[PDB]
Amino acid sequence: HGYVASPGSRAFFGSSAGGNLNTNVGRAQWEPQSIEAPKNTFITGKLASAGVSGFEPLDEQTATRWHKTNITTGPLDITWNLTAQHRTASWDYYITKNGWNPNQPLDIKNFDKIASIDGKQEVPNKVVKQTINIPTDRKGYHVIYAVWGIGDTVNAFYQAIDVNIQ
Ligand SMILES: [Cu+2]
């Protein structure tokens, strides 16, 4: 169990630690760490919730629905907080392509992978800090999809992150 705290994930921003910067986020208000589903679950319109019961409100998709963190292209620091550490296989990061439609359901086919970090089947610390590169053809509102792949289960934790790139 874990979430991306910086830049705050869509779920995390629904919690008090995240400033309640997103309203009406279902279970994400209280447990943004709990978006767990089998690996390689990428159902169109169900990326933000990973299809998980009680996280459905996260799947709404419009240009103005969600709070964005202002960022630049180039390096971006990602910080996870893990409420329950688990042996880890992988950390994968995706971002929406230039030209994507922020008023349509999220579809993984409209993202590129932009980073992949091997977990080495070790147990990470409670705070995990990684740096990924945001490609320079992205500007304005984009969604980063951060996926923590568990080493000793068939599951992963899924974190959609709303950013405004300038
Ligand atoms: Cu867990």
Image: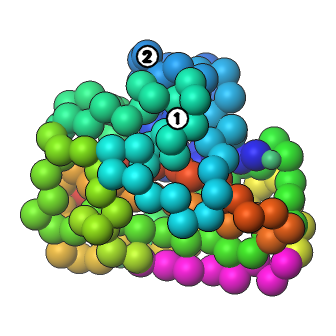
The image shows residue 94 at horizontal and vertical percentages of: 41, 68
- The residue most toward the top is 24
Q: Are marks 1 and 2 in contact (CB under 8 Å)?
A: no
Q: Which mark is residue 152?
A: none
Which segment did they paint magenta? 114-121
Element type where label 1 sits in the image: loop
Image location of residue 7, percent across then percent down: 49, 49
Q: Is mark 1 within 8 Å of ligand 1?
A: no
Q: Is residue 66 visible?
A: yes
Q: Which residue is mark 2?
A: 24
Among the two numbered marks 1 and 2 on one chain, the one whose residue lies closer to the N terminus: 1
Amino acid at circle 2: Asn
Residue, x 68% and y 74% (percent of image)?
90
Q: Nearer the viewer, residue 56 or 142?
A: 56
Query: From the viewer's perspective, is 36 left or right of 50?
Result: right
Rendered residue at 26%/37% (across/down): 61
Residue 117 drawn above or below residue 166: below
Distance between the Cα atoms at labels 1 and 2?
A: 10 Å
Q: Residue at x 69, y 82 (%)?
A: 118
The stretch drawn in magenta includes residue 41: no
Q: Give the x, y percent position of residue 139.
A: 18, 61
Position in image of residue 76 (x %, y %): 46, 66
Q: Amino acid at mark 1?
A: Ala
Q: Give the camera-side residue of 35 and 16.
A: 35
Residue for badge 1? 11
Q: Choose top left, top right, bottom left or bottom right for residue 33.
A: top right
Horizontal side, residue 154 vs residue 75: left or right: right
